[PDB]
Length: 224
Length: 224
Ligand SMILES: [Ca+2]
Ligand SMILES: [Ca+2]
Ligand SMILES: [Cl-]
Ligand SMILES: [Cl-]
Ligand SMILES: [Cl-]
Ligand code: NA
Ligand code: NA
Image (cartoon, rainbow over all chains, first blue to last red; front, side, top):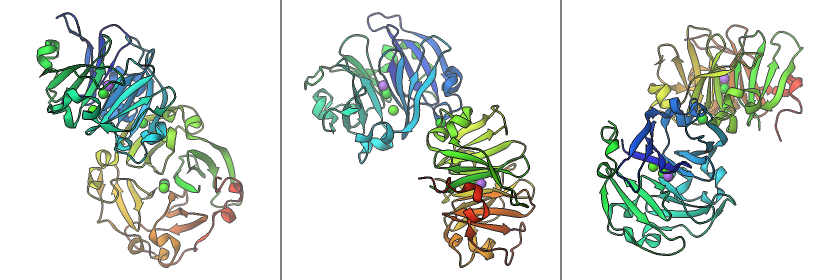
C-alpha cells in the first residue's frame, strides 16, 4: 500500500497521489515545511465521478502523467485514458479511452511497455514524457505520438541512480513545479532528482524516507 | 466479423446481437418468418451512453447473458459488468463493475474461464446459466454464485453437437423466449437446440446458415 502513481497538478505546488484504489491531493510544499493534505484519502470512484463505473474506479491507477492544461494520462495494467481532471471542481471527464496501451502508443507493441507502465513523469522540454518499466525507460512526445529515442536502461539516462534501489525500477513519479526537478518513489522511499533533458547529467544523491519529507502523510501511507 | 455475443431481451421475441464494436436489436421471430432489424447496426458507445467511456464502448462485448428483469452480464476479455439495458430507452446504466471475472465469479479462479468467456445463455431453471470456453462448458447459479457441476466437455452435455463444427467451441449464444430452446453461433452458422436442464437430449435440427434463418441480417453479417 504505497504510492503507485502520481501527477503534478496545474495548480501551483499541488500533486495527486494514488494508493491502491484511493487517492490524495497534496500541497507538497517544495520550499516550505507546510505540506498539507488538501483532499482525501478518497476512493477514486467517489472523488472522480467520471471514473466511477470504469476499471480505474474499480482498481485504481497504477501510472500517470500531466500533459498540458488540466489533462492527464492515467493507466491501469494494459489500459489507459486521457482525462480532464478539472482541479478542485466537479467537472472531471474522460476525453479519450479507455484504450489498450498498444492502440494509444503503437511504438510500444512488442516491448515490455505494452502490458503496463510502472511510472511516468512530464519533462520540461516541449511535449516530452519519461516512462519507466522494470529497469528500462522510454522518452516520448505525447503531442505527435512519437518515440523520441531507443528504449534504454534507466542507468544509461540517469547514471546518478546506479547503486540505489531505483536502479531496477520505480513504482511512481511526478515532476515538480520547480524547473527540472522530479520525485521518484519506491516503497517507503523517495528521491528528489535534478534532470536536464537530452543530457546524461547527475544529482542526486539522497534516497530518503517519504514520511520525513511529508509528515502530513503520517497514517495514510502505508495503506494496510 | 460475425456474431460475438448475444442476449435475450425481456421484451418478447427480441434479442441483442454484438458484432465487433457494434450491436443490432433483432426481432428474431421464433414462430414466424417476420424477422426484422429494429435498431442498428450502431456502435455500442452511441447506443448505450452508459458504456461510451468504458472498455465495452471502445472494444465491444464478446460474451453476455440475460439475468432477470432488464439486467444482463456483459464481458470483454477478462472483465465483466452487470448492466441495466433498459430496453427501448436511454435509461441504461452499469449496476456493478467493471470487475475482473475472478472477482465477480471467484469459482472461475484457476480455470480456463478466468481470462475470458466465449459465449453464454440463460437457462429456464432457477438462476442457472450455461457458459462456454473452448470445448468446455460450465453451469452456474448467478444468485448463489456457485458452480452447479464439474466443468465438462460440450459433447457430454450436448450430444446433438457431436460431429458438428460446434464440438470444438462457439462464438455466441442466446436463450429463446420459447422454453428449452437456445441458438448457438459460429462463423456463418447457427444451431437451434432443445435442452433439458440436468439431462441430455438426442436430435434437433442440425447446423444451418444464419442468413437462411434470418434474411434480415443479409448485408450486416459478416461485417467487412
Ligand atoms: Ca506504478
Ligand atoms: Ca464470443
Ligand atoms: Cl506515475
Ligand atoms: Cl454470448
Ligand atoms: Cl472501463
Ligand atoms: Na507520474
Ligand atoms: Na449470450
